Length: 258
Ligand SMILES: C[C@@H](NC(=O)c1ccc(Cl)c(S(N)(=O)=O)c1)c1ccccc1O
Ligand SMILES: C[C@H](NC(=O)c1ccc(Cl)c(S(N)(=O)=O)c1)c1ccccc1O
Ligand SMILES: [Zn+2]
Image (cartoon, helix red, strand yellow):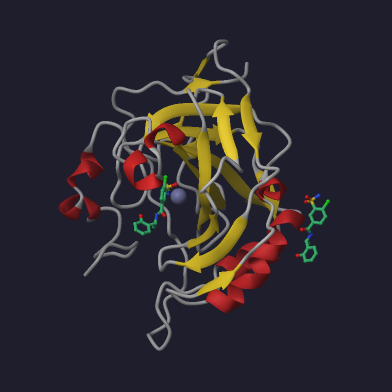
């Protein structure tokens, strides 16, 4: 009876196995755009993905991860609110059963159809497992998805999903370029938070882009054909794998833009 997103194992239950669920810097949050403060000291975000070496895509039973070789400084995030260099380890999404929900962060209570998380670890801690034990261990670049025109840079991901329909399936996924998932603008909001999935560790500097990307209804429909279950188990679609907004508590959200 492990954690998941259902009535009996979903977000309202997680605190029993992971008491930090009720902690002081939990994610996601609602981004109140009028309360967020413009911070002219914030730097432009530096996203240097030219040498990203994607390796594999995995259905882990909660979402799917596009994994990267993080054994060298090849795909790194710096600048913005960050001190030092953070290396890309994986990306994944959270999405809904319907276009009106799916994002984890919200903007003035608006829910997007999905949310992309590009997960990076601080190179001062040497790898991911050590980084997650530190309050400045991770930086996640969060990007909202709305349904409209297709995102051509997403299609290579969509087309491999048939091969990882079920939990524990992986496929080689090389030469994928995550630059094709970004939006024009790197304007962002930032705040200190946590993993949005168990173990919910309070180790993340969140960097949420203001500009969503557009994906087509056909693209998100293919996300919703995935399975939480492993092969030869009763079908439970892959949908609504999002944690709701958590209390902001004693935090300030800062904006990079006026
Ligand atoms: C579900 C999946 N989670 C991640 O891989 C994950 C890692 C880092 C971050 Cl920062 C995030 S997030 N959503 O905050 O961006 C999610 C998972 C797999 C295996 C064990 C535990 C576990 O949580
Ligand atoms: C639709 C997809 N297209 C691209 O990945 C793609 C091709 C050219 C370009 Cl320029 C881009 S872009 N501008 O989004 O970075 C993206 C695709 C291209 C070739 C084979 C399979 C595919 O799914
Ligand atoms: Zn996530």
